[PDB]
Length: 57
Length: 48
Image (tube, rainbow over all chains, first blue to last red):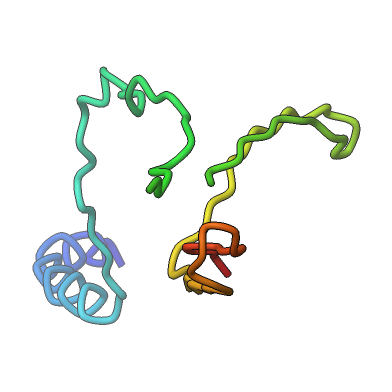
């Protein structure tokens, strides 16, 4: 019964087929690789509030 | 005419100071002439 190990080693190539099968079976996702470089947050502006355009006559 | 006004009020405790100015646009203007004599009373133009 020693030939079990010999047979498994010799026939091990079929695991490539098994890998292809499980690859086809598995669902897939992916990445949108993130950007670095938010090193400078930006404020709005120097903003001053005032009454609008008065309509004089 | 443009009328300004400032005030404050309460809003969940946080005293809010508010400042506003009101005006009008699309105003109609009526011209009434009661009489033409110097003594007569007249309004050349009143807004509505």
